[PDB]
């Protein structure tokens, strides 16, 4: 079932630079097409699993994002058909080792250690598509230890969800249960061991995660 | 329930790739080896088993072949020591890390992800599964690759800068590996372009071979 998509889904695709105010806080520039990177299936941390800090970062950031879960195999589809391939949604955190990412960008290296480590994708319960007639009218929020740190409106996305789906599908075929993370609004920032993150989509879902270090 | 490793590309979730693992490839790229292997990812839909085409992306004019040994995981592998790492291997496959090299040069220059260069649909042509029992030492293999009958790449897995047990241990500490995940262990020298309708043949001497046609989609 899609209600447990993180258990069997193979691929995670992430969009970068999709909120103008996040682009500004990063001091980057918006390109003509969305930036894409990948996370492995073992990046998923469903509720009840910890956010795990990698030992090689001293600057682990939260990033609040809407995930789009695919309901059917999606290969090179037009924008106008792209929503037909969506099964539903989930709220994700694109946990990011920001210090590692800065080095990767500077040296022209892959973004893997910065973005694609174990438990780098905390994920909410699945929200069926029927509950979200317009994914560009959602409000996202995130708290650390009870204090609000990120909020965003999906109406602020530079690239629309039907564009993202179509764009990704032409580069990488998407299977049933693959997710696309659609980028973070402004307000990214560090977390430390034992922080409690609470996050949600207003009116639809919330989730709580503890930041931990590996006990192995 | 469980599915056979003989068809790992059909159900396996993740592809992890090592960069800069053969000194003579590093030289031809004019790069440098770091203290640790470079890692990048491919999606499950990068897999092109025999009988499927290599698909050229529309956005490249310089699609390169890269000949690599793949290590297929047989058991869930989380943060394991080097000395235990081979216990987690199920077997092997020969892969091509198809690379849009023009796109990769731009990505490096702009500090962007290597995704469009490395991680597109059909970017991982893959041989038949070779069970671990047939390869007691994966660092004593000879790899070869032909384009239209002409030899273009050959390599010896003894030349790997980082060993397979090191790579598995290193990767497992960063990214937990599931049963049926593959690790591509890097290319020897001789990478080069292919064009539409080229025939690629490749093999591990004495163990496996495979043939792929280069096509454009639909
Ligand atoms: O680059 C990113 O990850 C983003 O914009 O969310
Ligand atoms: O960087 C690479 O792809 C390699 O060395 O195989
Ligand atoms: Cl990358
Ligand atoms: Mg995957
Ligand atoms: Mg992000
Ligand atoms: Mg390679």
Image (cartoon, coloured by chain):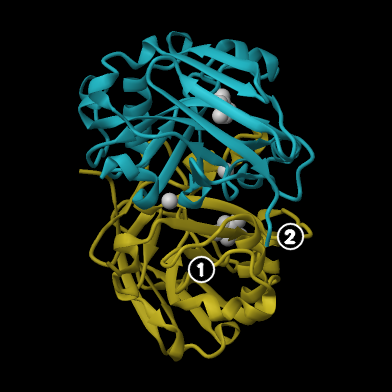
Chain colours: A cyan, B yellow
Residue drawn at the location 61% of the way across and 11% of the way down: A21
In percent of width and height, residue B182 lies at 47, 65
User: Residue A197 placed where, x, y %?
Assistant: 61, 30
Residue at horizontal 34%, vertical 74%? B5
Task: Answer left or right for A70 relative to A62.
Answer: left
Disc 1 residue lies near ligand 6 with CB under 8 A:
yes
**Crowd class of label 2 (few under 14; some 14 to 19; many from 20; radius 10 Å):** some
- Numbered-mark total: 2
Q: Which residue is mark 2?
A: B36
In the rendered image, the vertical position of residue A147 relative to residue A7, given as above or below: above
Residue B199 image position (x, y, % from top left): 32, 64
**Chain identity of mark 1:** B
Disc 1 element: strand
Read off the chain for label 2.
Answer: B
Alpha carbon of mark 1 to alpha carbon of mark 2: how far? 18 Å
Q: Is residue A173 visible?
A: no
Q: Name the residue that disc number 1 marks.
A: B68
Identify the mark nearer the N-term, 1 or 2.
Answer: 2
């Amino acid at each position: 079932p899609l209600s447990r998509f993180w258990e069997w889904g193979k691929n995670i695709v992430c969009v970068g630079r999709n909120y103008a105010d996040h682009v500004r806080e990063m001091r980057s520039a918006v390109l003509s097409e969305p930036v894409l990177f990948l996370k492995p299936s073992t990046a998923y941390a469903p509720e009840g699993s910890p956010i795990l800090m990698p030992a090689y970062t001293r600057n682990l950031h939260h990033e609040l994002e809407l995930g789009v879960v695919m309901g059917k195999r999606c290969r090179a589809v037009p924008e106008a058909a792209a929503m037909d391939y969506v099964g539903g949604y989930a709220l994700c955190l694109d946990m990011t080792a920001r210090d590692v990412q800065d080095e990767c960008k500077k040296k022209g290296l892959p973004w893997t250690l910065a973005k694609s480590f174990t438990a780098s994708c905390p994920v909410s319960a699945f929200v069926p598509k029927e509950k979200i007639p317009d994914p560009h009218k959602l409000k996202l929020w995130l708290k650390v230890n009870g204090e609000l740190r990120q909020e965003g409106e999906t109406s602020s996305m530079i690239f629309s969800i039907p564009y993202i789906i179509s764009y990704v599908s032409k580069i990488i075929t998407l299977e049933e249960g693959d997710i696309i993370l659609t980028g973070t609004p402004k307000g990214v920032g560090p977390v430390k061991e034992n922080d409690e993150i609470e996050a949600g989509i207003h009116g639809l879902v919330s989730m709580t995660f503890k930041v931990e270090k590996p006990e192995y």
